[PDB]
Amino acid sequence: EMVRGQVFDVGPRYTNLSYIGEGAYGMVCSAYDNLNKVRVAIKKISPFEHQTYCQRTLREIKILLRFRHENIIGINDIIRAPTIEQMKDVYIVQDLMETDLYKLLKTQHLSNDHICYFLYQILRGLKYIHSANVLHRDLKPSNLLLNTTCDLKICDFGLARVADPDHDHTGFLTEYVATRWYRAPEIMLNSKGYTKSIDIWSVGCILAEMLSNRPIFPGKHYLDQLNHILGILGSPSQEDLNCIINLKARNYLLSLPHKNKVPWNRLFPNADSKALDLLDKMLTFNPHKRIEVEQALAHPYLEQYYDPSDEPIAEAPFKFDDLPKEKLKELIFEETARFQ
Ligand SMILES: O=C1c2cc(-c3ccnc(NC4CCOCC4)n3)[nH]c2CCN1Cc1ccccc1
């Protein structure tokens, strides 16, 4: 069958296709799985015309095949031609979810009980990812899927990287890829986004969004983003400026008139007080003082859900993090053999 003028050769195991979502290099559809008797999500990927989408495809497949967690999307099946030459697209079968947090946030008011449960699930998923030495780098509401009982799952590992704190520093205003509204401020100033602290910042942004149903730092352009953050957080202290050695970055910060911190209580007067305290910790301008994932789970805001024993970590971390689209087709092919 075909969806929206796109051929969908996922037969014959899956039938009754329905459109779900779209990607730059692909399309997401719903279908009935005959061999398991339930509805599922199938993701048609055609990345072979670009070396960039291939990296993402490879990255994503390798990670998801290696991860196994309640709060992380899994791969049920991988469909593709039986030969290198015939392989035009690749179909990823996954559990069908009811919605995503992005959609939910535009239509629904979240109760405190919901915010707490969702935050806990994101943290539980995040802890497992960070324990594998992996950075997601693209956490946002659209990448968080929900089912009808409010089980949360993390998806889209295309931009994921192995953590590299040693190689993180960079110059002022260095190009980034991740979604702007969830960019930590150090990305703009001196960071490549090779630390776990970047995911924490995005999750803080997600917390604020769940609190108000609006993005907290909706910057129009790359540097605009910085101003949105500083507008709320206020001018960084001396200690935090001392952490930024690049003169271009430091001098820009010094050139800004002093900005006073806007209290969270003023921004979210209906918010739970324990929630706002955690929000403050996650949205800390200094990455080094920013709360870590395990500490966040231990915060009193989440105490009704906190159980260290029931928050697993990865068995095998990722050891290490130019290939043309050709050799990238070969690997994807090699990584997908399991399912044929
Ligand atoms: O990967 C995805 C993906 C996975 C799902 C998904 C999975 C499970 N279940 C549901 N259910 C949906 C029901 C309706 O409300 C929303 C969730 N969606 N959706 C998307 C849209 C974004 N892309 C990006 C992408 C797509 C193709 C190629 C490259 C990249």
Image (cartoon, rainbow, N blue to C red):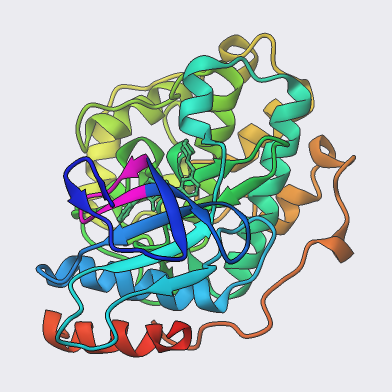
Tally of numbered discs: 0
Our reading of the magenta stretch's main secondary structure is strand
Q: Could you tell me residue 203's position as x and y percent?
A: 55, 43
The C terminus lies in quadrant:
bottom left
Residue toward you, 225 or 56:
56
User: Image point 39% across, 83% down: which residue?
Assistant: 336
Residue toward you, 23 or 291:
23
Q: Could you tell me residue 32's position as x and y percent?
A: 51, 51
Determine whether 290 is above or below 85 in the image: above
Span highlighted in magenta in the image: 19-28
Q: Could you tell me residue 58's position as x and y percent?
A: 33, 76
Q: Could you tell me residue 299's position as x and y percent?
A: 79, 43
Q: Quadrant of residue 304?
A: top right
User: Image point 58% across, 26% down: which residue?
Assistant: 210
Visible in this render: residue 45?
yes
User: Image point 49% across, 71% down: which residue?
Assistant: 77
- Relative to 244, 216 lies left or right: right
- Does the stretch in magenta take in 27? yes
- Does the stretch in magenta take in 192? no
Residue toward you, 252 or 307:
307
Visible in this render: residue 233?
no
Q: Quadrant of residue 42?
A: bottom left
Determine whether 142 is above or below 277 in the image: below
Residue toward you, 83 or 122:
83
- Relative to 224, 321 lies left or right: right
